[PDB]
Image (cartoon, rainbow, N blue to C red; front, side, top):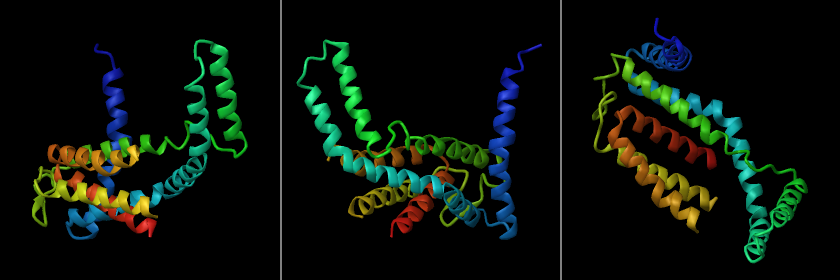
Amino acid sequence: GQDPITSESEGIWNHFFVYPMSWLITTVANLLNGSYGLSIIIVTILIRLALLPLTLKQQKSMRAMQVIRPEMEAIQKKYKEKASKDPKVQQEMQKELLGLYQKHGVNPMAGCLPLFIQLPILMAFYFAIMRTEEIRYHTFLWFDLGQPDYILPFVAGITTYFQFKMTMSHQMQMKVMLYVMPVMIIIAGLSLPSALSLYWVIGNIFMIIQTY
C-alpha cells in the first residue's frame, strides 16, 4: 500500500492546524449570526492577543540591538579592514561579538523566531478560508471573503506602510520596510482571497494601536 507519510503528515496539518482555525472562525461567526467578516476581525485580534507576550519580547530585544548597532558594526568595520585569510582572525572577531552580547545578556539568532510563527498561522488561516465552503462566496462590505479583490490588498499595503512609519517615529532597512514590504503585500494580496488581506489590515491596525 502507498506510504502513509503523505496522508498522515497532511492529516496532522488538517486536524491540528487547519481545523482549529476553521472551527474558531465559524464558532464566532455563528455567535454573530453568520457574520464571517466580523469573525475574521475578532479572530485576528484574538490571535494578536496570544502573540502579544512573544511580540513584546521581540520588540524589547530589537531595542537592545539598537544600542549595540554602533558597537558591533564597528567591530565588523574593523575586521573588514583586517586580513580574513586566517581562520584565527575570524575567531577573535567571534570572541569580541560574543563578549558584547554577554555584557548585556543579549542573544543573536533569537527574536527571529516570531518571524517564523506568523507563517503557519497565516497558512492555517489561508486553508481555513479555502476549505470552509460557507466563507467562499460570503460577501463582506464590497468583497467576497473567499474571492480575490482589487481594492483591499492596497489597503493592506497602505496600513503596512503606516504601521512601519509610526514604529520608526516611536537607512537601508528602513527603505526595505517602508517600500519593499508594502509592495510584496499588495502583490500577494491580489493573488490571495480577500480574507487574507482583511486579516492583514486588522493585524496592522492592531499593531498601530499597540504602539500608541
